[PDB]
Image 1 (tube, chains in turn purple, cyan, red):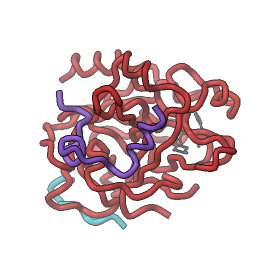
Image 2 (cartoon, chains in turn yellow, blue, cyan; image 1 turned 45 degrees about the vertical axis):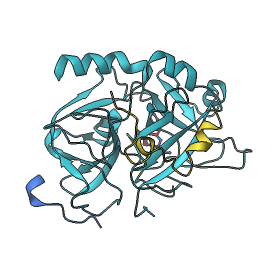
Image 3 (cartoon, chains in turn orange, yellow, cyan; image 1 turned 45 degrees about the horizontal axis):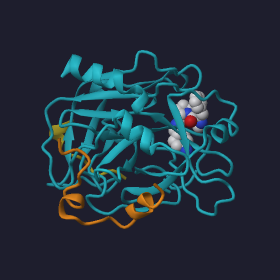
Length: 26
Length: 10
Length: 250
Ligand SMILES: CN[C@H](Cc1ccccc1)C(=O)N1CCC[C@H]1C(=O)NC[C@H]1CC[C@H](N)CC1
């Protein structure tokens, strides 16, 4: 149901410092 | 160097 | 983790530390996939060559942690195990094929800002994301070199072509394994190292914004050696056993 959505990041629309590196490779 | 955990959990 | 950096607070709320009671020490990483279930590598619990065979009373699960050694009062939650399930076909005699184990917690952990389960991939998610060149993320409190860090470390690593994985080792690779790491000529580096065993290799789906656990830190030869790669348990390929165990046991 709510898996994989982080309280301090996705739920607040905040990105961590390197997850864009991940998405840029997809 | 681990800190002592609360005895209860042991 | 070799050549990673300090994690941000709440960045991997599924990271679990497997902690030995006596002597009190970090055994392995692990991941929280529901309020009652933890996933790790089977070699974290059973590996007869080195006489390792831990049962439920030997261990504690510590969830919500950031600091490796401190008891994070009011943040972390410690749990005892009810039952350990190792894949009946885990191959500790040869190449650690099917390196995977589930741990049933004694009581549900309550989620919080620092404690939250990762998703397990379905076929479509695995098919879209587990492609050569795509990066995933490994986290852990393990060795920084082939000292130990004060806080959780994190590194982003590219999945590698199965030919290249196969040509880097003499150990037999199976379809239940994938390898990841930078090539010796890519400039960037990084790897899991001792104490990171059992921890999560995760990827963020660009379709629905969720983090999925694609692998488990399983084996390698050394840490961050050139021309060598980290090998991970392929979680989707073993998902039918996972589902079978959770709905046959709670
Ligand atoms: C150190 N090398 C062995 C190689 C091996 C692989 C498969 C079967 C037998 C031997 C190993 O990885 N392991 C021997 C049994 C357990 C496992 C291990 O140590 N895994 C931990 C890894 C953490 C990350 C590090 N880069 C590599 C070792």
